[PDB]
Image: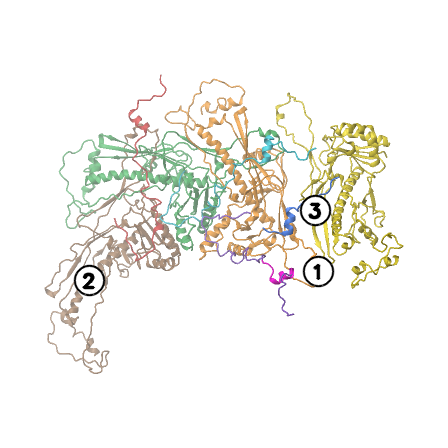
Chain colours: A red, B cyan, C purple, D blue, E orange, F green, G brown, H yellow
Amino acid sequence: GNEMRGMTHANYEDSRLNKSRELNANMSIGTSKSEDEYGRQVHSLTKQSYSDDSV
Amino acid sequence: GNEMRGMTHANYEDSRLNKSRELNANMSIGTSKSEDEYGRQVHSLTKQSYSDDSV
Amino acid sequence: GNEMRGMTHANYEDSRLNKSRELNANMSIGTSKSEDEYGRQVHSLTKQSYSDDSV
Amino acid sequence: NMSIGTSKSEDEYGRQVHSLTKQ
Amino acid sequence: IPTLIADSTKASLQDFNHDYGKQWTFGENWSNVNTMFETYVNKYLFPKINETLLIDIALGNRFNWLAKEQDFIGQYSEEYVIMDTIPIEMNLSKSEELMLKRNYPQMATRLYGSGIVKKQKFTLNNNDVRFNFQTLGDATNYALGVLRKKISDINVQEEKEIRAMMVDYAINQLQDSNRRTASSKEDLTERVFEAILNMQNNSAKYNEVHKASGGSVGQYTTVSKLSDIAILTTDSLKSYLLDTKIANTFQMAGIDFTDHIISFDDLGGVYKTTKDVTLANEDTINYLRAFGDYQAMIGDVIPTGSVFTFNVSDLKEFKGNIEEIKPQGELFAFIFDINALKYKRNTKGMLKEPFYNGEFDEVTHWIHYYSFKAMSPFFNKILITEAP
Amino acid sequence: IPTLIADSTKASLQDFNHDYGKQWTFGENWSNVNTMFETYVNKYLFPKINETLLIDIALGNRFNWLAKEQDFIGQYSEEYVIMDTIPIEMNLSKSEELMLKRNYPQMATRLYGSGIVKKQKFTLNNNDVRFNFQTLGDATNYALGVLRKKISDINVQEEKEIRAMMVDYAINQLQDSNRRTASSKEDLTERVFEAILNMQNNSAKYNEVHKASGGSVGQYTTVSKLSDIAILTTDSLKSYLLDTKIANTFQMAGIDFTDHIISFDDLGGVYKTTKDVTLANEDTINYLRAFGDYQAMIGDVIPTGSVFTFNVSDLKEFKGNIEEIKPQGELFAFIFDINALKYKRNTKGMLKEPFYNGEFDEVTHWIHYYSFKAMSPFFNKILITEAP
Amino acid sequence: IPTLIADSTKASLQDFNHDYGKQWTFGENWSNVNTMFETYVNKYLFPKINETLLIDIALGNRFNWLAKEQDFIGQYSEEYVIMDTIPIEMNLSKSEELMLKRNYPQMATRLYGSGIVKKQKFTLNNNDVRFNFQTLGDATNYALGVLRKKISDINVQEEKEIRAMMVDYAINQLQDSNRRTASSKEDLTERVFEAILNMQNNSAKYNEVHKASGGSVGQYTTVSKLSDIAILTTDSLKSYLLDTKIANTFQMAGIDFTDHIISFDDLGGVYKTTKDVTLANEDTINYLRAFGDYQAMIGDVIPTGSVFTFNVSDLKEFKGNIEEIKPQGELFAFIFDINALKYKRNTKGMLKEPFYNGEFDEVTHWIHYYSFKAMSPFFNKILITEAP
Amino acid sequence: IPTLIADSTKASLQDFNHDYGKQWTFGENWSNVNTMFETYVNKYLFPKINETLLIDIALGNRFNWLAKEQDFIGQYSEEYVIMDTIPIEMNLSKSEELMLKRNYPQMATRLYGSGIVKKQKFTLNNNDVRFNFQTLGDATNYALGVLRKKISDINVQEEKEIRAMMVDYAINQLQDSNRRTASSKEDLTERVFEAILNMQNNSAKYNEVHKASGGSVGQYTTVSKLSDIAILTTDSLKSYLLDTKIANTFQMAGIDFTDHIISFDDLGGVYKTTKDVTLANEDTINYLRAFGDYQAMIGDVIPTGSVFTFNVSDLKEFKGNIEEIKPQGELFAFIFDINALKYKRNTKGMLKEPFYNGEFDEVTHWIHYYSFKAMSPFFNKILITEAP
């Protein structure tokens, strides 16, 4: 990975030309969530507690 | 309620463009007032004391 | 008696367009002062004390 | 057979015209 | 679509509209087949709505600070200025009887008269509106929302009328001497500077005492301090000053008059009829109703000089009979002493008491207020406008 | 060229592809002569490779902050505003019956609808893939590289969709009052200054209430605060403002709007179908497959309004039926209140479970997520675009 | 006198270049009269020289930082990127067997293996080089001076090749989307400003993945971070920026990109052959010798793509078969991601052993090194060049 | 002695009348031997006066009560009354919409005008009035006497004007319906006694609301209570009315008919100018001066309708231009409600400050007061006059 280096003895700073704030890599979708209650029941039907009006 | 966020590493401020001082929601008509003496008499004819020149 | 309000978030000062120092409500002639000794004497000849000529 | 009342003091206007107690 | 989707008889409205209706019902059958709500998996469950949102916005009236509460008792008002007297020399030659000779104070006066009473109204159903909202809380927000909107509207209209008053006065009423002309916007910025300095001096040119009754003979000299001077301009002109004139000048340490400027986008758009127009069509009344005019009905006459505050020109009757109060030519800078505005209001008992119709479970509420807007000739004021 | 390099009978593909194959082999003899690999000193030695680098890059979504996690439970949603009512004069000649007559609050409302689910699939072989890489560690890097890339692709697509949504809304939905024309870049930058100021004062011109259900005739006045205003522009314009307008101006202490800009190089590039095309050719499916559409097969129907996000125009069926959503002309500025976007996403359980085919030793992995993107009519928006 | 000076029979060269020569010397009388070196006091003394100075200079390579030392061990290297997959909507009417279907990850790869093993040699005589220098101390300096000059040539030449590689890649490899045209220097400076911002966005337009093996139909989106963008231009442009742009602008804080620029006096100067040329002419082989190419001999073949680094065009065989790697039009601003360059070197055992020729008394030192330069297709690049 | 008395050389007047009068006096001898004043005991002493009476007759305005002090600022007087509404039956069968019906109150009005301001003055001389009185105390009484006579004059004049107003109103500005005719003096007494009772009846016929702007159409029923009724008749007529037995029965009951009836001998003696005369002769100004008119001068114009209040008919300018305000015919009874005579007056700072001439030692004092006199149309009035 080559690394750009300073080619000038002194310069005005380059801040304004940077879009690191606008479109950073860290701003991205998160994949760590686990499924909601409905999902867990679809997979295992583990909740047998409530069937709503019955009998 | 989306909120806009900063999209520049550095910039000059936007105070001059801001027009909150000129026109803001706080500057509005007040509805808490109660009726004048004439109005109260129109509504109830409470005051029976004076009828001006008589007889 | 309406009076103006600022209507701008930030502005450079308006000094230099103001003639308050040059002309003002004050800077006016003084009504309150009483007659000089001569005047008071003309109105009522109060000072009967001095006459320059000898008998 | 009553008579016109001879005197009462001048209204506020009368006194201020005579004196001009400016204020 | 299913037949149920299009069946009027099954509707809640029918139960309310007809004098007798079926007290008992066994529910109808719902299907999403061949309709917008189709769901791949079920096909027999009713559509479900997650949320309802008010999106209420609060609006203000720029000129509120100016408004002065007053009693609503008498129709007319007057203002007057004592005219100037030039000091004269002592001529002791004159006869002693001059003491008896009488000089009287002189004055110039103006009469400005009646006000305008305006009203708004809204009715709340209670019985059938409840069907619309899932929770009582949403319905209560609905009722606060109509009241809040009603009040905001009063503020926007008052702002429009004060802005229109000034634009109308400047274009037509203002004394010819006061008018000044700028060839370009750059010249205008200089013209503003000259006027601000000029009107702080003791001079009779800026005041319109000549228009007032006693001004024909004599002079009145008034001075206007900077603290009071204010300027009305279009937004594009303010943007010019900020974007280019202020940005370009090397030193604007002092010499910045933008605090004073009141800038409006359109600075026009309030429309005034030029001939009597009589409402004659159903379509016309429907347009007016959409802007809140319940009172309007066919055959009513709108007199000349009536101010609509919305664009009624397109409608048949008002096609050639409407004119717009607007600046002419895009350079407008009416600079005036603030004291000239004369805005008075009476909002005592503004929210009139509600009326409840027991039949129909409805309470109808009203808001009424008085507003007088006028401009005084006596104070200093000069308009800078594009050269004709 | 030696026969061995050309011969395919000895390929690994041959061994895996066919039902029975040679279990035992004595190695073939290799020569570099008359081949790209020729080495002067030693012929007869197999080519040797030093690196196999991944070159993976991480991409992000600019608009991620707007996304708000939500449950996936119900489909429809709604929002409404109470429309403006102008104060009306007290006629007083009207019948006393007016008190009884009822007029209700009037409102305008929108229904948005359900979202769209999206999926991506990758399978890892566990046999032939191993032949490609020299070390076990290189293969593990390869597997993570596919997952890492997959997420990045989703971010990039969502950004494109939000950017395209805004460009499409401006191009089609906006009214004449909202729209403005800029002759040149200098004029455009000034126009943008005017817009920021203009949209901070009360105006019904920029609302799209008319499109909403109750707004066909009527007005709604809304005011947009500065913090909210954000502007979507082409990079060419930002480069100009910073390079020329800002650099040249003497005083920019205030008057800088670059914090608000959301500059993108293209804006255009997301295509939308028209006319209900139906896939009919192998060549078409092959192009779509290259861009990731495993699902597509000949005979599937692509509905009108389908948004591709890649250029499908050249392919036969879409030749005259695809339209690009883009700014018309180089100059584009859509200045809008931020509140209008309405972006919501659900990522719960995004990474679905793996499925392993014991035959072939391959595991297929899936990523499934839900996205709803929409634009609200009620809030203020203004388009400054190149004059036609 | 002139006649003596003219005679070459007396020359030292004749003794050295012939098998037998006349050993005895009878001296030649020398007279300074009517010659440029005459002195007033003594008119027969041969002219005497005071100093013999070297004027050696040191030249360095701009690009040395990029170079990475490596063991010289294996011929090839490869690198790859995983191609983009757009998310696909959940059809839900697809056959349930789709789960079984296998979708494999896709990628694009490049193989770059190469080396050039460049060399150069210098020979020090010990007989006849002595004739030239009067003090033995200067003669020793002459020997050190050749070694240092040989090293300076390695550095200058590598710089030319890296500079030429970049100009060549941009001029030929880049796609239409990457290319931009600038009419004048002010237009160019704005374009450079724009390109810096364009590269920071996520876009596939500037990638060269299409050239790579798997990218023929699909797309890859990469983002080039600032701090890794270096721009290669001519000095005339850098001078313009400093003299007329940076100097004049009021607010150059923040907008100066000159740290990135790698300006060269003249980007062109390296020539690449097209066609094959055999060195038919003796005059050509002599010219190449002036530049240090002892190896060249008549009848050798120069392959297509040979890079000369000096102007060989005038020579007959290369008259039509040479093409200069150069910018077109004097406006060139190839902005690129630094990662793309890939310069590697092996300098172990650079100074090879000396070989003493007993006959002729000459040492013959050699310097050998290995250098590999290549440019990667995957990273973002833009070329702004003079409008045709 | 007759001759000494006759000589005017020896007079105080001669010295005061002319400059340079005689300073030294040697007394003149006095004898009463053949003259009046002769006394038996002492013939030569000067006649001596026991007393100077200073008889003063107080005169008063009978109408002074029923005068309302006003604290004047402003000029006009409105005087409204509210018109009658007759009670109506329940009519429960009528539609319930009758609840909504405006039923606004109605009224009549009369704008009277402004009041004249009158003045009187007396000059008191310190130097010569002193000669007349024996003691200082008598002279101080004389000064009080002149002020009191001035006050008495205001009263007689106002009484005369109020009486004249009634005679003029009855003769000219009266509703014709109110008038009645009496053939004989005896018939008049019957008519007048019948009328007193008629006023007490509650009926609209007597009042003049038919005039008074307001309503010709509706009715206002006014009643005049005993104690608020009075009869303006000539003195002879009052004697006839009192003589009748009815007057005696009233007094026995307790109502004093004698106080109520008000009489003047002729109801005449106040004169009205007709024809706009202008003063032209010295003799006239002298007559007016005898009656106290310092202000009048030759060339002053007396407007038509000026009320002289003394007989100026003999004077030449007014010879054909004066008409007396008097009942026509001997019989004249005007019976009116007392409240009708609006007689508002302002008496503040009544005695204005003195002015001291200082030459002649004389002080002039002035009395100034404001009087407004008018008659109201609303109360009951009947006029009984001899038949034409």
Q: Which residue is mark 1?
A: E96
Residue E316 shows up from this direction: yes
Q: Amino acid at mark 1?
A: Glu
Q: Residue furthest left?
A: G358
Disc 3/disc 2 C-alpha distance (Å)? 129 Å
Answer left or right for G364 relative to E26.
left
Seen from this angle, which residue lies furthest right?
H34
Q: Locate residue G282, reporting x and y percent.
A: 22, 62
Mark 3 — on which chain does it sit?
Answer: H
Q: Nearer the viewer, residue E78 or G49?
A: E78
Q: Residues within 10 Å of mark 1 (few under 14, many from 20)?
A: few
Identify the chain of the residue marked 2, using the numbered disc in the image. Answer: G
Q: Which mark is residue D7?
A: none
Q: Can residue H252 be found in the magenta stretch?
A: no
Query: Which quadrant of the figure has residue H110?
Result: top right
Image quarter of the C terminus of chain H:
top right
- Which label belongs to residue G148? 2
